[PDB]
Amino acid sequence: RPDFCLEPPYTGPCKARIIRYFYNAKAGLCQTFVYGGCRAKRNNFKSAEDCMRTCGGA
């Protein structure tokens, strides 16, 4: 859970039904969410495997 693991989920103004995965710093585990399509943030992944191996790690 390095730096790109602190800023919380940010969907932004758009609401494009683009489902994505993110790192839940509230409990220390990756989880699922919805991306608007514009103005995303660092906390952003495409698969839980991706977020766990990248931000999760441990």
Image (tube, grey):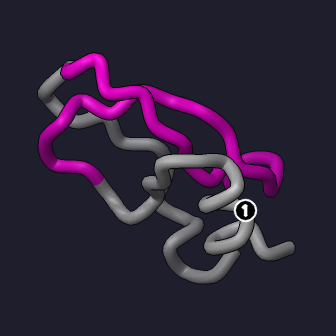
Q: Which amino acid does label 1 sit on?
A: Met
Q: Is residue 43 above or below residue 10?
A: below
Quadrant of the snapshot with the N terminus: bottom right
Magenta span of residues:
16-40
Question: In this image, 22 relative to 20: left or right?
Answer: right
Q: Is residue 34 above or below residue 51?
A: above
Name the residue beneath numbered marker 1. 52
Residue 31 in picture, x, y percent from top left? 67, 39
In front here: 29 or 8?
A: 29
In front here: 8 or 45?
A: 45
The residue shown at (14%, 29%) is 13
Question: In this image, 14 relative to 28: left or right?
Answer: left
Which residue sits furthest bottom? 2
| Quarter holding residue 35 | top left
Q: Does the magenta stretch include residue 39?
A: yes
Residue 22 in picture, x, y percent from top left? 55, 48
The residue shown at (50%, 73%) is 4
Q: What element carries label 1?
A: helix
Which residue sits furthest right? 58
Residue 15 in picture, x, y percent from top left? 20, 20
